[PDB]
Length: 417
Length: 155
Ligand SMILES: NC(=O)c1ccc[n+]([C@@H]2O[C@H](COP(=O)([O-])OP(=O)(O)OC[C@H]3O[C@@H](n4cnc5c(N)ncnc54)[C@H](O)[C@@H]3O)[C@@H](O)[C@H]2O)c1
Ligand SMILES: Cc1cc2nc3c(=O)[nH]c(=O)nc-3n(C[C@H](O)[C@H](O)[C@H](O)COP(=O)(O)O)c2cc1C
Ligand code: SF4
Ligand code: FES
Ligand code: NA
Image (cartoon, rainbow over all chains, first blue to last red; front, top):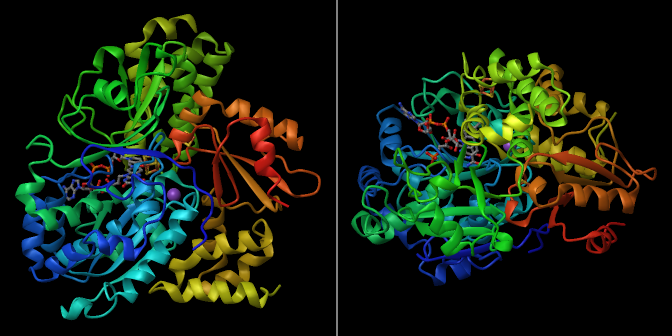
């Protein structure tokens, strides 16, 4: 009943799907959820074969909401081609700067996530599922534990669920400070009771994951879509947004906007529409300088008319929109991005370990005007050399946003020289 | 060293929760830090035995996970987000306000061992920047008068 204090993040929807309940900043318990027809998609799914559910999730065109956009049906298909036992993992590590879309599902509509996990686990033949939630989401952790007990009490979990013969237990694990533990193989190691160190891929978790068994790892938002695909059928789900990038999408908008918060919109919405049509424009009506897609990409004011989809020219990523205005120093902002990667590298790979450290250390010198000419040259080189030999996406992107600021805002970097 | 019954019962609960005992390490350590206000170096050996893991394994886990502090005892941990959105919206104003109220800077502990400022990476509440946590509770910093009132709730 009593949970730790959680800020009341503003949430607005045009689709009334993922935020049907989560648009209200409060826990929605099982009675409230059931009144909205909750757990009926699970009932329908338990009367379908695991194979039909995979086919439906495939045909819906649902792509991973964690940031990489891998087709969900396709992922499940790879796992089920491998013998059992299989494991299902809900990734609730959400630690990307500017990213707060998942937590509002967890904290306000936990039964939407739970129902999605049960359908997904049934579809892949997993009798054991996990929620790995970042340690900095303690309220989300107690909210999920309470909602899981409510589901067990209503017979949605445990042995022979609703007389289907399908068994399922959901275990909630907590992270403990590491951004890298959201990387799906580091998450699996942490779930195994070890340090959050990413594994060399391939194998992908679907071939060899938790305890070396076929494992599906899906983001909170991806899983929250599964009850909607089953409830409305894949065809009606595909009517939402463009047919090539279908369904609802959560957009966590922050920074220099009048209305920061989470927006549920179709993926054909443009970045400019997200800021100006939905987030109320900029604070003080000051000109947009840049948009940071988390700690992954940097878009200039010349790139605002792009769609918020998984297309090559689209925004992509998690859909995270951090708005910087004309008075925000791009180098000071780049320093914040460099400091993030410095703090989060697991240090397994030498160029990532040294590269993340040096990029932040040299960028600080540059910013403070204490950099030598060799420091400027070393900084340029280290930034273009974090990726070599990396075994996870962190080393591959630790220099991406910063390089884009160098290319898109050369005038500002030039004054720091 | 022996864990108090009230804590030992909570640790046994986390250990019997997951299908394998070793899967409970992080939940056990969070519980140890909640109880003591830090990770006492002495607690690691009985925990390793309860998890059926070697001490070296437990030591490496404690070293890896940044939420765990085996150095400073503190009743209340003020986690201050130092990442990009919060820096843009006023981390420095929040840290200035904290220095004025408690007399401490990040990484420091108040003389009475009541409060410790812990600088942290993005806390996933960026629309509410600048964000801070006081143990498990999370808030948007508004001003010094406002922060003063929040901190007064922690006795
Ligand atoms: N949401 C957050 O808080 C957060 C934080 C940090 C990073 N990220 C995101 O993480 C993304 C990178 O993730 P990644 O390294 O997992 O990316 P990825 O493109 O390599 O893979 C995405 C998913 O598809 C699966 N997959 C890919 N190829 C496969 C294949 N051949 N066979 C089977 N499965 C396959 C992977 O196992 C994974 O589950 C970034 O775009 C970033 O936005 C998100
Ligand atoms: C360093 C790093 C951190 C990641 N953190 C997260 C995270 O917090 N949440 C998430 O769902 N995916 C995260 N990912 C992506 C996962 O590895 C993976 O792609 C995803 O969980 C699969 O789910 P999806 O297909 O539903 O998106 C991270 C990737 C990397 C490289
Ligand atoms: S690229 Fe960096 S974060 Fe990823 S496994 Fe290598 S050292 Fe660790
Ligand atoms: S940058 Fe501080 S909460 Fe995200
Ligand atoms: Na984590």
